Every structure is written in C-alpha cells, then in structure tokens.
Amino acid sequence: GPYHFSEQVGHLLRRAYQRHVAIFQQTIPDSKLTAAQFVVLCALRDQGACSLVDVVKATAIDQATVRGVIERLKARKLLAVSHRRKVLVTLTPDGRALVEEMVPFAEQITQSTFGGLNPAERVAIVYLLRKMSDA
Amino acid sequence: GPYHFSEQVGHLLRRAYQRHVAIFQQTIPDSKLTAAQFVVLCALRDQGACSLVDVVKATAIDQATVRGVIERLKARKLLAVSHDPADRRKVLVTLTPDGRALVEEMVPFAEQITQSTFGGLNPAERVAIVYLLRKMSDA
Image (tube, rainbow over all chains, first blue to last red; front, side):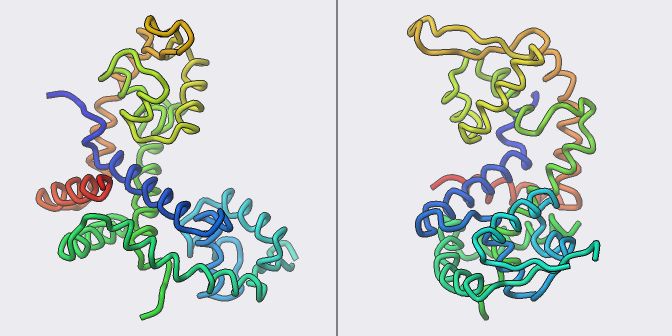
C-alpha cells in the first residue's frame, strides 16, 4: 500500500552512484585523486582550456564544488589558472600525466560498476540513464 | 574508442542522480529538508528504534552523511536520542511525533518526485531501471 523509500528510483540512483564512488576509491592508487578531481582533470584533458561554466557544463558538478576542486588541483600544481573578471583553466603536464596514469584504472572501475549486469543488462541501463539525464 | 569520462556508466549515474536531487529540491515543500534527511526519516518510520549502523544498513547511506543528518534532525526536534536498553553505552535514534507527522506530510510529494524522476520512461522502462539499479547495487 504505502510509501517504501527503498524501492524508489531516486534512492536506487543514490546507492548506485555511492557504490560507484566507493569502487572508485578502492581502485584508484592511494587516494591520489577523488572522483570529482578525476572528472575535472578529464574534462580539461579532452576539452582544453576552460572557463568555470565550461567545466560545470562538461562535468555536471555544481559550481561551488568545482571551484573547490580547481583550488585543490591548483595547489597540487596539476592545473593552471589565469585572468579580467573571467578566468581560464588548463592542465599542467603533471596534470596530463596523472590523468594518463589513472585512465587504465578508470576502465577497471567501469567493469566493477556494471557488476553482475550481463551484456544486455549493461546496454539497457546505459540506454535508460542516457534517456533519463537527457529528458 | 579511447576513454571519455562522459560516455561511461559512472558519469551517467552522477548525472541522473543530480537530476533527481534537483527535482527533489524543486518539489519538496519543506526547503530545510534534504533527500538524505528525508530517507533517514523514512527509515525510522519503517524500522522504529535504530542505531547509527542500523540507519546505514537500512539506507546504504554512508556513516558520515548519516551522523550529519541525525545531528541536523536532532536540532529541529524531528528525532530523539536515547540509550540502547541492551547497552546503556550504545545510542538509539527514534522518530519524535513531529518527525512522524513530517514524513506523512511529505509522502505525496515524494511520490510526485518519483514520478518526475521517471520522467518520460514508459511503464516497462520504469520497471527495467529499478530492477537494473538494484541488481547493480547488489554484488
């Protein structure tokens, strides 16, 4: 009859996300990188120099988090920032090196994330998530 | 093809979960209440007295997020803290009557949120994704 939160799609997205992030933490050597940091670095590797809303657009991460992430990555010298109200952001060579070094592990993470799902299941979930985030 | 972070299943989960939380925030009347807060409250409604790990188990929300939720809900007097009758040392959280009312008040909206989140998925697609997400989250 009533509400069961555990069987609701919204909750089941959180678990699946959360599970993905935990897998990412186990799999990435020595908490070198958070998942958000990795995503921002990838966006920069693929796209090139970006504004802040470029990075938000690219990564689907809220602006306040991205600002934080860029600051931490600036500190670690993995990216560069430059002006005069608007800023650019660009990979440093260590930046790109770290990304390249982690991309073999990120592949691992994907398989793990898909879990028990069989190949038809894998296609189906990706189809459904695409169809969900789009519309 | 090479690795693009955006095509991969981790990102689509991220995007779809962002969409859900935006939907949650837009439609929930009580603007102080977070998706995590709400879920914890539903778990106490369904389970009665719970330890911190009970809530982590019931919800699969991480322990840091849970303590934070509990602390926030303690402040608004929506849950009470007691001692475990088994262990005078170990602590229990329990809905207050106010907590129970608010859960009941939000149920319609939660249901709407679910509907919005499914968006334009057809009745079979709604079943398929709930199933695949559970299968994914097990093992």
